[PDB]
Length: 129
Ligand SMILES: [Cl-]
Ligand SMILES: [Cl-]
Ligand SMILES: [Cl-]
Ligand SMILES: [Cl-]
Ligand SMILES: [Cl-]
Ligand SMILES: [Cl-]
Ligand SMILES: [Cl-]
Ligand SMILES: [Cl-]
Ligand code: NA
Image: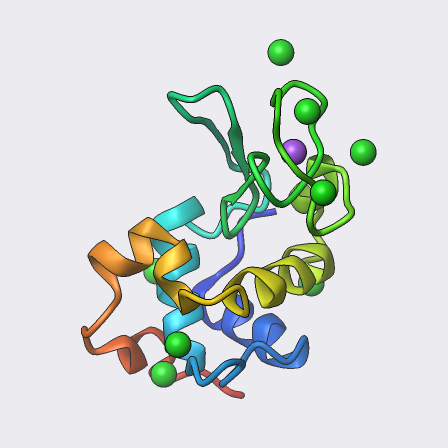
């Protein structure tokens, strides 16, 4: 599923991501925009052979099991395929664990390079929330 901007803002908020670990809703929408372009089915291979899955491009190196990432963990206790669902529950639950791991949203390199410090509220501008 390819979410609209406000549609995703609403789903993230409904699933309790808004201000989770002190990160306003705009941060999470901005991250999803640059990680996946709001596409739940997005997958991208890393140079190290791990893969990033879903709206927030959760990495198989630590967080989910895809069966082809030697040496990795599955700290979210899910198949990476669960992270591609039209329903964002698995992605949100797993993102809450990631953002709690110590480095906040810096875990998402695209968030650090493209969202951090910017006017992230623009991402939820005009949304009925
Ligand atoms: Cl957009
Ligand atoms: Cl915001
Ligand atoms: Cl694996
Ligand atoms: Cl393969
Ligand atoms: Cl594990
Ligand atoms: Cl699995
Ligand atoms: Cl959803
Ligand atoms: Cl933080
Ligand atoms: Na893994």
